[PDB]
Amino acid sequence: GPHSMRYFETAVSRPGLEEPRYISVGYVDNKEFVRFDSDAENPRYEPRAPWMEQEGPEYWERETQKAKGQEQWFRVSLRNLLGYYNQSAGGSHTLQQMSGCDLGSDWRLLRGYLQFAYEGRDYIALNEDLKTWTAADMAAQITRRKWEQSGAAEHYKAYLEGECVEWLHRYLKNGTDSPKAHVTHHPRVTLRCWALGFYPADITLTWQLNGEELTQDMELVETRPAGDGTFQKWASVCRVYHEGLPEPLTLR
Amino acid sequence: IQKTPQIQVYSRHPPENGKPNILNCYVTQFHPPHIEIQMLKNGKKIPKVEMSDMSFSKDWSFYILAHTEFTPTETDTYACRVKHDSMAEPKTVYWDRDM
Amino acid sequence: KAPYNXATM
Image 1 (tube, one colour):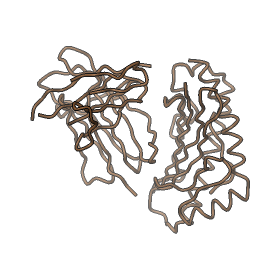
Image 2 (cartoon, chains in turn purple, red, green):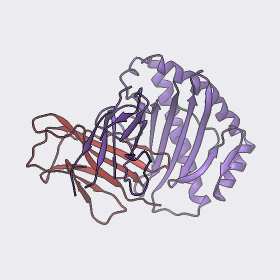
Image 3 (spheres, rainbow over the protein chains, first blue to last red):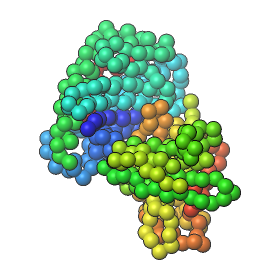
Image 4 (cartoon, rainbow over the protein chains, first blue to last red):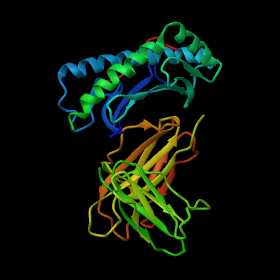
């Protein structure tokens, strides 16, 4: 089926300490498999997955050396961004980065991602073509002019189309629960359809007793994790659609 | 911009008295990341609360998962108390076996 | 494998 890999890097400067805290988290198929934290014993890339433990010692040395590089990269830009926005000392700031590859059933890349955000808001992003940049603030114009004049897109394109899709394949060659549903009858009467113990989070509930879907009221909650590798969801006011289901459920 | 957290507390399984379980406290849609979370059992904080690593959603807001194994009893109440900059005082959310 | 940025902001 379809697969993916993502790296959520975060750097936060806080009034009180000299160097900002830097975290990097990796996901294979929307499941965490490795992490780095500059606040650790002595920071390094540790496995967060059962099937990741079999990686060579040379593998964690290169990855940890890279994270030290990103750390510095985030420390300089964070200082650069204070000037772009005419901020002074005293506040807390966040630079975030999301990169990754979505590949398909043919094992080839479908779309890569490279996107940055400052203070939680979008800052600059590599488009779907991997060649151009999208920048919203006028402060991000300085950056887009810098990167498109220093060939950043072509470098990131080489990672997305090369290292990303290659290594995600190697990770997957090292390693689908359907929901059990109930309905709560409690009258206030409002009905609630629960979907529990499914993986992945691909779920879709719906309320149609008359054959027509409902959005007037129809209060929902977005899929949330249970304390283990599953997820749950309920809907208010019951066909349940899931990738593991051969036929959507029916309960009333 | 800062975003007040969205807290919601819920059980793994439908709670039946005598069975193990996991109590969850899902905190989402907040910014900045600095946040304090504690789960309560009848006003007393629950020690040994395994808590997720922090990642962030597609809108860049942060989320984090707090959970502990537990065996529910019908007289005792469990709650989640959260400390964030965007709130004046800590906010506490009680688990209900309802919905 | 983690990416590795070139030019700063």
